[PDB]
Image (cartoon, rainbow, N blue to C red):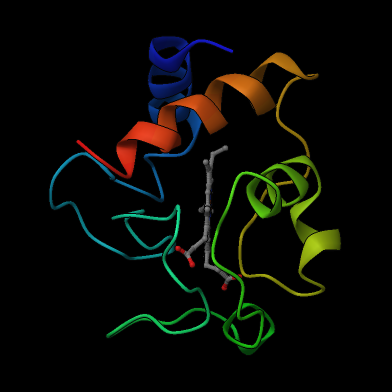
Length: 104
Ligand code: HEC
């Protein structure tokens, strides 16, 4: 989808939990300070539920799709409170934004 639409719409419904713009906080969502290529399951402070901690992926543009589509399914007991996003466009917009949020 669109990178800007991604970041806007992200911020609209995600930033509440995830202030990935600089140096927000964790606090009910880790600030997504470099996902793409970073081995999941190991955050140096707040490292989520064990269900996610145990996941040991590399938050790539596959795992991110499956998660954002169906996060409770992807991880059976994430502390993420999300269940659907819009339709489809957002799963393409968001996952365009974060693909450079990981590098701005
Ligand atoms: C607060 C109620 C949340 C909202 C709204 C969103 N997310 Fe979230 N997210 C939340 C938690 C508590 C966690 C921790 C993981 C766990 O299972 O315990 C997460 C995690 C993520 C991650 C991965 C974290 C990492 O290992 O880096 C991603 C990629 C992520 N969340 C993305 C994301 C997006 C884009 C959101 C809007 C559509 C969003 N989250 C909202 C809590 C919450």
